[PDB]
Amino acid sequence: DTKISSAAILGLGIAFAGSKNDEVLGLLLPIAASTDLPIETAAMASLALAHVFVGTCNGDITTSIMDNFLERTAIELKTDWVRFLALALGILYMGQGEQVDDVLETISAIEHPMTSAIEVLVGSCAYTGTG
Amino acid sequence: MQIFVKTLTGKTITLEVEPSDTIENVKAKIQDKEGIPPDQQRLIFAGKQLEDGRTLSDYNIQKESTLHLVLRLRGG
Amino acid sequence: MQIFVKTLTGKTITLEVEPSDTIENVKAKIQDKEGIPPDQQRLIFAGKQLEDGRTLSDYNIQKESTLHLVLRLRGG
């Protein structure tokens, strides 16, 4: 059934929910992209932040998350998590903002047609899509 | 020429360079502006990524060009 | 001064060091405390990874400084 994991992260999310402390992040980010430890507790964490920084998007984030879709590295393992990850990159922003438009420009500027699926996700959303 | 550098955080930088300038020289100028180490930088421009050594001329990078700068894949 | 070393998910170790202390030296103090060998350590601060040799003074690392102890292992 439900893995005690969700219950854990859930508590943390409600813990530093309203606290723009550069500490929690200084710990989550690494565990999410410290280029070492597995990618298990990593994926989840990534979402944890998204929930908090759901509104105000930081830099160190989009930076690591971005440098990931490209270099990826964090390859120690693999199974199924690109779904939740991609989702974050989407809600990563508030919604109405050409900011995302620029980002896509970066993903397009670089090869790696593997993330294509994503380009269609974020793209379809926000601007350039509806009609 | 005066080229711009847009970071993935939310800020731009106006650096005065030239065509003969080597990407390496640029990265250095940045390290002096902010504090990011060369071994930890990623410059992208309309075309692809700028490799070290080459010159801004190779990438036909003109003036007022926006350079997408991104840090290495880390956490902190 | 007394610097702190927070582990990704272990504990916050406190070590008495100085500004003239070399990173390598610090890593040694940690290896003596826990059991992690230097060739398997990685002190990260404000996202800026500290290299061996340098001193806690070069990074301006003052007292009660929180150092993010991270692990690493790559080469191929």
Image (cartoon, coloured by chain):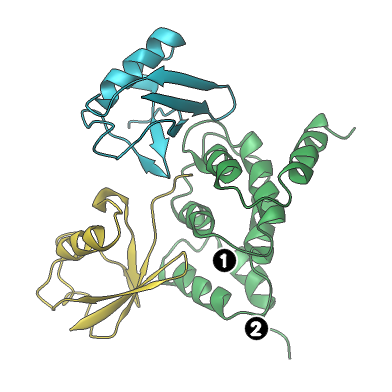
Chain colours: A green, B yellow, C cyan
Q: Which class describes the residues within 10 Å of circle 1: few (<14), some (14-19), or many (20+)? A: few
- Most foreground residue, B32 or A129: B32
Q: Is residue A85 left or right of residue A131?
A: left
Q: Quadrant of the N terminus of chain B?
A: bottom left
Q: Is residue A12 left or right of residue A106?
A: right
Q: Please report, as a chain letter, where disc 1 is located.
A: A
Q: Position of residue B47 (x, y in %)?
A: 34, 75
Asked if residue C46 is positioned above or below residue C42 in the image, the reply reads: below
Task: Kindly identify the amino acid type of the residue bearing the numbered disc 2.
Answer: Tyr
Residue A59 numbered tag: none
Task: Kindly identify the amino acid type of the residue bearing the numbered disc 1.
Answer: Ser
Q: Is residue B73 left or right of residue C11?
A: left
Identify the residue under disc 1. A116
First along the sequence among labels 2 and 1:
1
Q: Which class describes the residues within 10 Å of circle 2: few (<14), some (14-19), or many (20+)? A: some
Q: Position of residue B2 (x, y in %)?
A: 22, 82
Query: Looking at the image, can residue C26 be seen?
Result: yes
Q: Residue at x 21, y 28 (%)?
A: C53
The alpha-carbon separation of the residues under discs 2 and 1 comes to 17 Å
Residue A127 numbered tag: 2
**Residue found at the very far bottom of the displayed protein:** A131
Looking at the picture, do discs 2 and 1 lie on one chain? yes
Q: Residue at x 82, y 30 (%)?
A: A4
- Most foreground residue, A37 or C23: C23
**Residue found at the very far left of the displayed protein:** B20
Q: Please report, as a chain letter, where disc 2 is located.
A: A
Asked if residue B75 is positioned above or below residue A120 in the image, the reply reads: above
Query: Looking at the image, can residue A83 be seen?
Result: no
User: Where, by quadrant of the figure, is residue C2 drawn?
Assistant: top left
